[PDB]
Image (cartoon, rainbow, N blue to C red):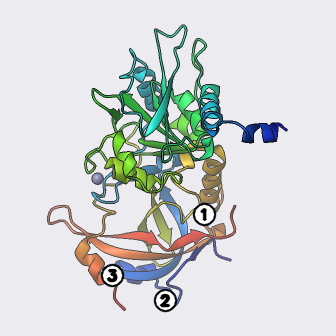
Amino acid sequence: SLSQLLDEMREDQEHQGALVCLAESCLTLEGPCTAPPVTHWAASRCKATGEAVYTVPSSMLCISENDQLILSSL
Amino acid sequence: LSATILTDHQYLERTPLCAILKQKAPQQYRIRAKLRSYKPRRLFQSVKLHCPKCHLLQEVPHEGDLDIIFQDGATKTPDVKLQNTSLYDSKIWTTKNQKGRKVAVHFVKNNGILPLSNECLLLIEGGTLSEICKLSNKFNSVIPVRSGHEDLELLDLSAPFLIQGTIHHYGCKQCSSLRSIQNLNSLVDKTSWIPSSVAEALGIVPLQYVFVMTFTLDDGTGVLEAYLMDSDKFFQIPASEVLMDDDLQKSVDMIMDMFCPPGIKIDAYPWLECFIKSYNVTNGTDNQICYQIFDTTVAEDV
Ligand SMILES: [Zn+2]
């Protein structure tokens, strides 16, 4: 009947009431808000403090327009 | 009996690397070699963000930098709104015990009515990254915003302009002049939240998560430096999601470990049958020949 209870009710507010609600389910408004999770790649990106990290100059990857025109042949 | 397969260009015949290294460019070949060497040795720094237009290669921002930006965003109180809430509704919480923090969640309206959480678009002010993370895993879209002096505007493009699940979406800071949030009314499809159509309405040109790698292949006649820049074809792992999930991060760890098993000899390495294109790069009147890997993906490895 709670199935049918929802039908005979203002759609605006069941949509309204269920939205601000999962939203307050996600907030931590009680004191210190929690700490987000980290996956083992993210945790080791914060300690790659030594050398230059692996990154290619975008010159070497951006294929020229005039050599790409050649490349769609045969 | 081959670790990577071509997804096209299978009418071509295999070219030896010794023949390619002395040839003119541009040209397209079919090769199969063993992965003797590759960079980076640390795979977590292989995911970057390519700007499709201006070909900008840049780094995916650090998560700790994201956490600081939203922790710093918690300040004073918002711009409320005005007779402006024709596109969205709103609900302001007041927090106890956090320097007067007051978050502002704004629910985008679909044609005037509010939808379910599975097809809704969230607009947060003063949320923290963790609260942003969990909001994203129950709602459909979360766009972190701030109170401008007239209308809700986006954050600095260091912070994502769109978050749906585990995918943060970034716009290029150099080739995307913003339009403010009230231009989302221009969407004809306000139930399906296409990141491309949200970015277009905001005037944002999105960056592309692409794996950027350098391979040193060897087929027995010579070694070659082939670049690998792709989004979600090679590893069958979407680069858009990889930095937010152990399972996908772990999966690309073991794929590289089967291309190049560290600890044994190259005799027992599997072949990588790839399709490469050569091209001429210019850095002045310098002129290099360098090779990108295309149309290749691993087979039977999930
Ligand atoms: Zn750009």
State yes or no: discs 1 and 2 in contact (Cβ < 8 Å).
no
Image quadrant where one finds the N terminus of chain B: bottom right
Task: Locate residue B76, reporting x and y percent.
Answer: 38, 14
Numbered-mark total: 3
Q: Check disc 2 and report its element: helix, strand or loop.
A: loop
**Which of B248/B191 is in front?**
B191
Label 3 in the same subunit as label 2: no
> Can the viewer see residue B128 in this picture?
yes
Task: Locate residue B22, reporting x and y percent.
Answer: 33, 81
Q: Residues within 10 Å of mark 3 (few under 14, many from 20)?
A: some
Q: Residue A71 carries which label?
A: 3
What's the amino acid at mark 3?
Leu
Q: How crowded is mark 1: few (under 14 residues within 10 Å), some or many (20 or more)?
A: many
Label 1 in the same subunit as label 3: no
| Left or right placement of residue B19 versus residue A42 in this view | left
Q: Mark 1 points at which residue?
A: B259
Q: Check disc 1 and report its element: helix, strand or loop.
A: helix
Question: Disc 1 is attached to a residue of which chain?
Answer: B
Q: Name the residue under label 2.
A: B12
Q: Which of marks 1 and 2 is nearer the N terminus?
A: 2
Q: Is mark 3 within 8 Å of ligand 1?
A: no
